[PDB]
Image (tube, helix red, strand yellow):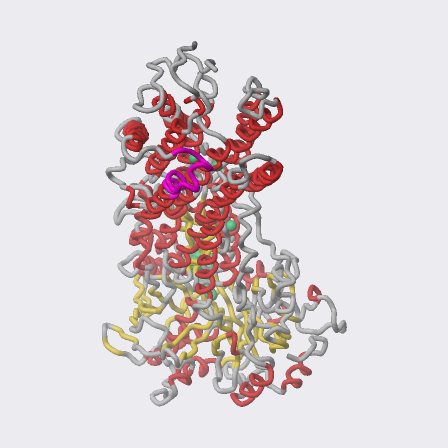
Amino acid sequence: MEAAHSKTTEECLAYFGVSETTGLTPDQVKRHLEKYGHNELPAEEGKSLWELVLEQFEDLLVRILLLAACISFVLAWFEEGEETVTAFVEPFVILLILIANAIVGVWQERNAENAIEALKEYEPEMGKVYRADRKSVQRIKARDIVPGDIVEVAVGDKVPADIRILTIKSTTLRVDQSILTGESVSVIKHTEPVPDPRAVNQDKKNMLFSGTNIAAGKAIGIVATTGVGTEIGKIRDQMAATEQDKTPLQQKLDEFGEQLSKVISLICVAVWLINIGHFNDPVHGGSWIRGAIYYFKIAVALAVAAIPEGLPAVITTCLALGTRRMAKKNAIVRSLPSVETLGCTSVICSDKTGTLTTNQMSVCKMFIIDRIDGDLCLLNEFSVTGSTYAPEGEVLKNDKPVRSGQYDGLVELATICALCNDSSLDFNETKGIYEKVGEATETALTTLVEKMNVFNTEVRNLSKVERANACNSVIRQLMKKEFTLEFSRDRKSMSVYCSPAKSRAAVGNKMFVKGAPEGVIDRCNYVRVGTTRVPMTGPVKEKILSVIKEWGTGRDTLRCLALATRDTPPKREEMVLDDSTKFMEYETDLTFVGVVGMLDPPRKEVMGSIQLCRDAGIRVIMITGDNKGTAIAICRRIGIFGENEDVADRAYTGREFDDLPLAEQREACRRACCFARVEPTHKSKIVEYLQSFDEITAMTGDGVNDAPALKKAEIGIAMGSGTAVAKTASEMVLADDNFSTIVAAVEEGRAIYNNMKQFIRYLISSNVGEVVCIFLTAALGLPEALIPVQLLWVNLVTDGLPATALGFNPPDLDIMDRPPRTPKEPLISGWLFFRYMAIGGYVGAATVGAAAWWFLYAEDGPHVTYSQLTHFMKCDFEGVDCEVFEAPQPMTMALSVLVTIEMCNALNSLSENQSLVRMPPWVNIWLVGSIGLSMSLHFLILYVDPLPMIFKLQALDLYHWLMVLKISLPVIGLDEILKFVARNYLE
Ligand SMILES: Nc1ncnc2c1ncn2[C@@H]1O[C@H](COP(=O)(O)OP(=O)(O)CP(=O)(O)O)[C@@H](O)[C@H]1O
Ligand SMILES: [Ca+2]
Ligand SMILES: [Ca+2]
Ligand SMILES: [K+]
Ligand SMILES: [Mg+2]
């Protein structure tokens, strides 16, 4: 880790004593490693403070409860009398429910963070280095690179460690450093140094920082420093950590929380004033104050009982739960809002190569010209065996094993593939498998060149390592690659300028081009036949294109490329290299050589996932830069279209899409499910259109040309084996490239919603009748139904654990067989309000009808024969009874029925509109236990003598209880009825 960039190329190569072309010797590596250590970080310590997490105490509400707990603590203190045992209890009953949800949050929160870390501890980062033990680049675990050895980076790659740029192989090099500095834009770089020693990161345009991605280009440089010395390792924790705020569903719910904070605020202040007549009253110390005060409590307590203190805590929990379950499916959630959003995704756009397919390419069919005679064009089509990148396979013609070098046309075909290629193979001894280094497509051609071996290079006895690139190196050792005109989506082809070694064909300089067949074929005026050349003709050009199409729409839906070569390139001088736009011109007046057909197998889980998406109401769109024929073919075989379904206007190409007027483009986007040969920004535009219909859309990519779209989309989904550039722009990464998970994600995203909607229904319909209880008893002639503590109780027993458990609710019956939720759909439909009201009604008038019941019809206390003796003012009002109006017997019956009916109401929230018969309590084994935990806690307060006085008098076991269930249970049938109205009816 030499402390500088200041010095130039030579000083760093010399500082570590290494050749840029060979790189460290296995010995040096041993040394530098012991000396400098493993290039990693202690970072493996991220684990939020034991308590840092216990911050379930910050949401809007809850603070309310904490406040109410304060005023309860001050009142309970001063308040004199035979109290204290009931005065000081109130506060704990208010924060005990907070403590309860607090835990559940912290717990399901730890497990989440805990699983997200294991997802990363699986699949270590890799880097490409140049070591002396191998002639060609080799990939090693990044933790194993050390300062000094040569390293190679390129488009999409994530910079493995701080590096002094020694040389830029491409005609330009840009990179994304925003993560470190801030500068949101491809920043340029160059070889020379900059005098300023301890200068600011943002200036060193001769470095690459560990953690930044390469925007465009390819460069080789020497590791200036690793480990913590990294200008990203020291500036590690210092980052203020930009953890975005709440998610769209939380902002939606936190707002709906204060919407009640208001309504409730009224209910309470109101319930308060609608007293007074009892302020100066007897029962209240006889004073107006004690009377007013007692009622501020009836309000305060009523609030703390109506404010869903478990709402914020639940969204949180449920979310971390989604994350944890995605992690389990090897899916990395990089953004909290993902799952919830996929849940209501109307359309899923997806890249083809890599995303929809395995990207495991191999050349299986290839052809050159055999002979030409008039309108008849004979092609020499060969077949190749070997589906991996292994340099083991044979070239067959008429199914007989041929000597590829026998055909001059195949020699050139091989020459072109080897020289016009920025990739290579690397033998991974650990798995004994040949791996690619660079873009799949190109690598495929490298393995091909190895299989052809047009120069019969003796390779029977070479190391599995030395074999990997043997044949290629030979073609390279025979042609000097002057410069290469980088590949660009505009012209869809790449070129390379080569000079003969020791000048064989004299100054015979050539340009070897390879690209999308159509464009390359169009830029060909000559055809090569053996060593000969002839002008391109109508019958030949059609023949060449016919076989390609045959290959692209068949069983094998091959991916194809044309190989051509400019025999007489422009004078090296008249060519400018800092403007891609000019390159297509340089690649003209070409000579067609041949074509190669690659196998690129669709991922097995795709078709299935595509199907389920249909059922879910998800539209699936394929966007690619590949040939439309190959595209539509692949789309049929994947499930986007039917095997013989006409697609005249549901499949377009870049050109076609652009020829359409703005108005139609948008329509084409809602109609088409396949866009091919799309230009650069087309993927993004296509996501904009779908968003201009107010549709939650998602993009799925693997490479850099997906970044834009991935960011534009509401949800970006990236592939684990894709580039870091796409992964960055993405909000989720399928670590294992399992397309199915996306569907699993959208499902969990929906469940998470329904759950919140159920938690709300319960929490609401209950609490409504809860207050409906007061505004029907405290204003209908009946005596007080409950008192302070008695409210803080039901609260702590029906708004706590049993509700939060609704978060661990299973996915509804046909949740993933119903169309996506409109981005505008209201949180609570109107009928839903009726549903809450009806239930709120009954529960509210079966809690009051249970108090009166006792006084009347009940075989206890008075009997005031159906009339309650009309009023309460009796202090001969019949005077056949004492003051049974201040009896506890009646309240206990009230408090207990409210509680029981609420838990009964809870069982009505396992699903929105589903008969308990189909989805029984045991679908959510947690809700059950929770219920019991609350139920048991009730009995204890009801019968364990020390407690009863603090609350009320023990409702006679049996009879009294039987009466509770006889009026509570109906709530379960009442809503069960409401459900039958929406299920088997309404729709
Ligand atoms: N490295 C390369 N050199 C020469 N030609 C290439 C090339 N990579 C791709 N091509 C050609 O250019 C075409 C367009 O490339 P582009 O990246 O836009 O789409 P693609 O099919 O290569 C990847 P995707 O299907 O995931 O969008 C490719 O289909 C191929 O015909
Ligand atoms: Ca409450
Ligand atoms: Ca309640
Ligand atoms: K995005
Ligand atoms: Mg791709």
Q: Is residue 649 above or below residue 453?
A: above
Q: Is residue 182 above or below residue 145?
A: above
Looking at the rendering, the stretch of residues picked out in magenta corresponds to 937-953
Picture quarter with ligand 3: top left
Q: Considering depth in this image, is 475 or 735 the residue closer to the camera?
A: 735
Residue 941 is inside the magenta segment: yes
Q: Quadrant of the C terminus?
A: top left
Query: What is the number of callouts on the image?
Result: 0
Quadrant hosting residue 751: top left
Say whether residue 393 is visible.
Answer: yes
Kindly give the residue lying farthest to the top in the view shown.
Answer: 876
Q: Quadrant of the N terminus?
A: bottom right
Q: Considering depth in this image, is 846 or 336 the residue closer to the camera?
A: 846
Q: Could you say where residue 26 lies in the image, as x and y percent from the top left?
A: 51, 88
Residue 741 is inside the magenta segment: no
Q: Could you say where residue 674 lies in the image, as x and y percent from the top left?
A: 39, 48
Q: Could you say where residue 168 lies in the image, as x and y percent from the top left?
A: 60, 72
Q: Is residue 141 above or below residue 895?
A: below
Q: Which residue is painted at 45% across and 35% down in the image?
A: 951
Q: Could you say where residue 220 lies in the image, as x and y percent from the top left?
A: 58, 75
Quadrant hosting residue 107: bottom left
Left or right position of 245 against 715: right
Q: Considering depth in this image, is 660 or 913 the residue closer to the camera?
A: 913
Kindly give the residue lying farthest to the right in the view shown.
Answer: 196
Q: Considering depth in this image, is 407 or 712 the residue closer to the camera?
A: 712
Q: Which residue is painted at 44% across and 58% down in the image?
A: 111
Say whether residue 831 is visible.
Answer: no
